[PDB]
Structures are given as C-alpha cells and as structure tokens.
Length: 102
Image 1: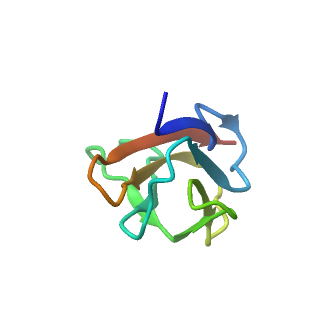
Image 2 (image 1 turned 180 degrees about the horizontal axis):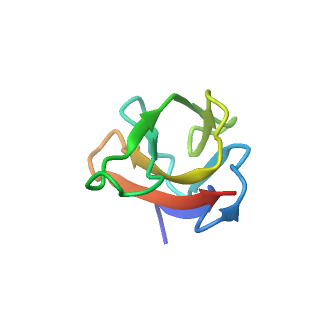
Image 3 (image 1 turned 90 degrees about the vertical axis):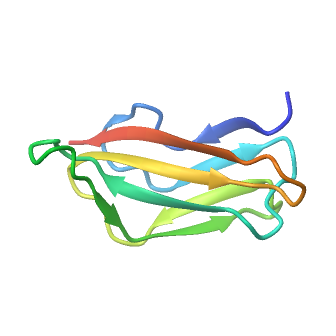
C-alpha cells in the first residue's frame, strides 16, 4: 500500500528510551509541511496532563524516511511520539507511537 508502511519508532517498547524514531513511507510525501513531537505521557495522576519534550525531526537521505531525534535525554517514564506526516498534494497521515522507559 502507499504512505506509511514501515517504521522503527518504539511501538509499545517497554524497557528503555528509543535511541531515535524512524518512520518509512512508500510515498515520497513530505515536501515541506510535516512535523512530529514527543509528549511525556508518564502517569495520568493529574487528569491526563502529559508534558511536551524537546525533540528534532530530521529525515534520512530520501525525504520519505523521517528520523525523529529526542534532543533531551529521555528518562524513565511513559511517552508518546505524536507524528504528523503530510504531502504536497493533500492527504495527511497523522499518527502516534507509545512506549515505556524503565
């Protein structure tokens, strides 16, 4: 199928911070209208209030290959990457991956 096909993000990885978050599209979408962020969804103790963390969105050689690098070292907790991929033409793919860090 076109669009998002493979990744190496952290799909329910429970153990350790992922080194980086790789996202691999069949379609060369992402002209210049894409982004991603990472929220520390640690514990919904105070009514589901996560905290947005500092991460950089890069790509590999081909602009179909996104590579998100956390800028701040990810500590223990629980965390969701929310990614927002988009093409020139139209047709977003917005999405997320959740993970736990021991």
